[PDB]
Amino acid sequence: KNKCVNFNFNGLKGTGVLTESNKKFLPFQQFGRDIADTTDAVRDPQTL
Amino acid sequence: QKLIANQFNSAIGKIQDSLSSTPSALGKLQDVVNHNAQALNTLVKQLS
Image (cartoon, rainbow over all chains, first blue to last red; front, side, top):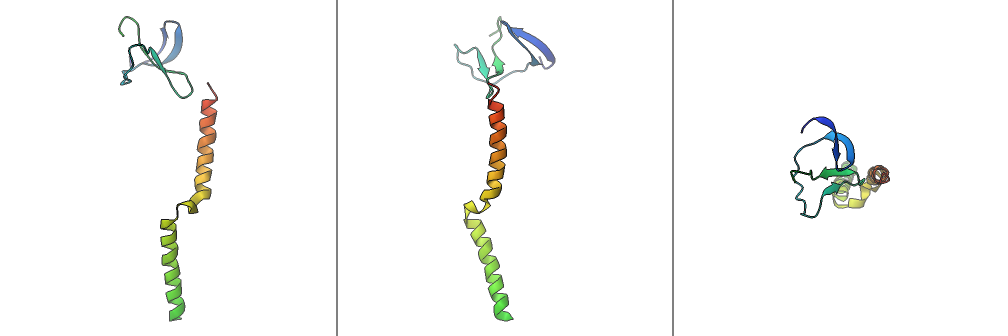
């Protein structure tokens, strides 16, 4: 966390910095999207 | 001279009040700002 890394979440490849979020996700919701519909938040496996 | 000075002062005060009470006076500058923001936001949305 808090460092520029290239991640992989169930095949979702990308590069960025990972931090905590206050996005009150619904139980069925897995990841969020921004205005441009690029992934903005994600729920990680093995930790929820 | 005194009458002209009084008329000028009253006109200046009335212009101040009219600008303070009319919202559509600054429409040209507001439209410039809105056009720039709208173009940039549309360019952002186009990525999806």
